[PDB]
Image (tube, rainbow, N blue to C red; front, side, top):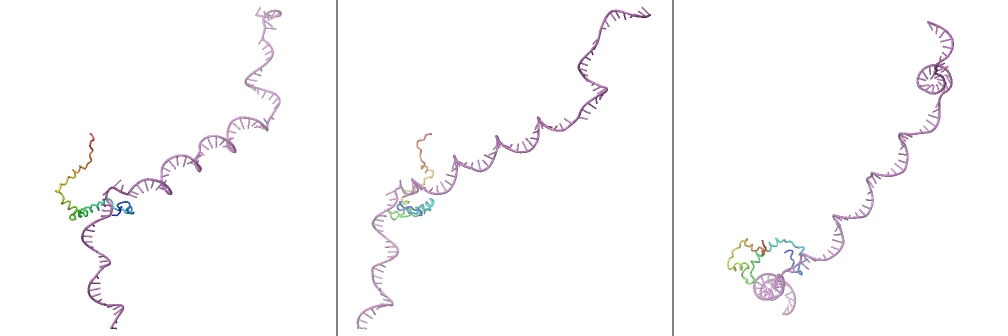
Length: 84
DNA sequence: CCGACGACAGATAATTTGTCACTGTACAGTAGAATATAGATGCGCATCTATATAGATGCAAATTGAGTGGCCTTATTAAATGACTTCTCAACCAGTCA
């Protein structure tokens, strides 16, 4: 991708600050595709004969029930001891 | 007759491509950021300038009131009016008469 910075400062492409082009919305639209079409569909290397997704789906002990989006309110931060 | 070179055919490792097994290495919070400089621009405060004088003064007409200088017939009489001055202002005795 354009604007690539290398794995460290000694390998930084000198054009990285001038050659940047993508916004966060482009990078996510590339990265999500890469994870859904390529990466989860590639071979689990320990096995050699299953995809990562195929091994996940077949590896569930049972199909879990989807949790309600409201019940993810367990994500809300707690203030423990404020007084009325 | 003997030796050298070309045509055609045949066999072959070098080259390239593909497949397969073993492996060094990055994933591990991290370079946008700090520190000088020149150069232009803008707001504020001071430091002059040039204009604008009205009040005071000097002077020169313009009367203005107040001076001063120069030029002029006279003698008798009479009347009138108004004045001034002077003078004067006794009292009983002696001689007639109806």
